[PDB]
Each structure stands twice: as structure tokens, then as C-alpha cells.
Amino acid sequence: ACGSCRKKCKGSGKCINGRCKCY
């Protein structure tokens, strides 16, 4: 469950707690 969190964070990202944070 992320919602294109990888594209939003184009590359290595994180999608948890309903929050998409990038690395």
C-alpha cells in the first residue's frame, strides 16, 4: 500500500503509516 510512492520519490522511497517518504 503506497500509491506510486516510488515515482513520487522517483528512486528508492518508503510508503508506510499512510506517508510516502523518500530515502
Image (cartoon, grey):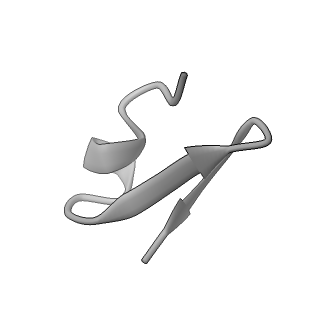
Which percent across, then down, holds residue 7? 26, 45
Residue drawn at x 49%, y 56% is 14
Q: Locate the C terminus and report the quarter of the image it occupies.
A: bottom left
Above or below, comparing residue 13 to residue 18 in the picture = below
15 to the left or right of 22: right
Residue drawn at x 46%, y 25% is 3
Name the quadrant containing residue 18. Answer: top right
Residue drawn at x 20%, y 63% is 11
Q: Residue furthest right?
A: 17
Q: Residue furthest bottom?
A: 23
23 to the left or right of 12: right
Above or below, comparing residue 9 to residue 23 in the picture = above
Which percent across, then down, holds residue 9? 36, 59
Above or below, comparing residue 1 to residue 6 in the picture = above
Above or below, comparing residue 23 to residue 17 in the picture = below
Q: Locate the N terminus and report the quarter of the image it occupies.
A: top right
How many numbered marks appear? 0
Which percent across, then down, holds residue 21? 57, 63
Query: Looking at the image, which is closer to me, 1 or 3?
Result: 1
Which percent across, then down, holds residue 6? 30, 47
